[PDB]
Amino acid sequence: KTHVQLSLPVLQVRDVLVRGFGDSVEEVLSEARQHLKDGTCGLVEVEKGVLPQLEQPYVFIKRSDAAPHGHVMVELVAELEGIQYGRSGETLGVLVPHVGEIPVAYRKVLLRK
Image 1 (cartoon, rainbow, N blue to C red):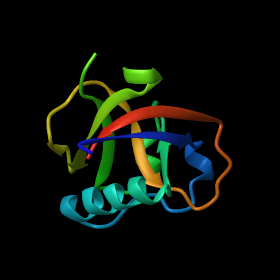
Image 2: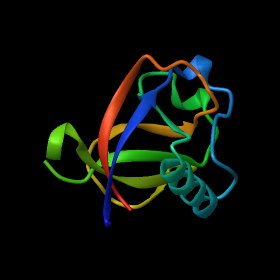
Image 3: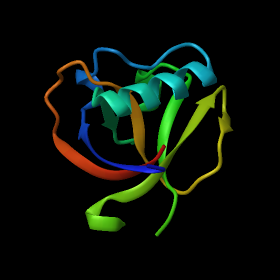
Image 4: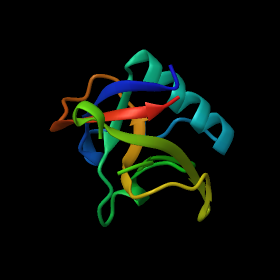
């Protein structure tokens, strides 16, 4: 399937134990896609002061369309030193590994895979 229905645990930035997916744009997109498939991917909602508490490169989920079955269609865009690899809509949040942090909510998305 080109798209997969996922429910992503929304984590508070100060709870996150592993604050990024790796060290290159290509690695973080790779790792983010693997964790999304394995159900080991969390979402941090971007507000003032969140991104400097996480590790670059960042992986964003961005709205790719204007929401089948409640699930917003999203795609991945990475960012490193102010350059983004990908072009998409509004940021829903930044992806991080999930290693058992208690979420505050769940974000239903349809992921272009």
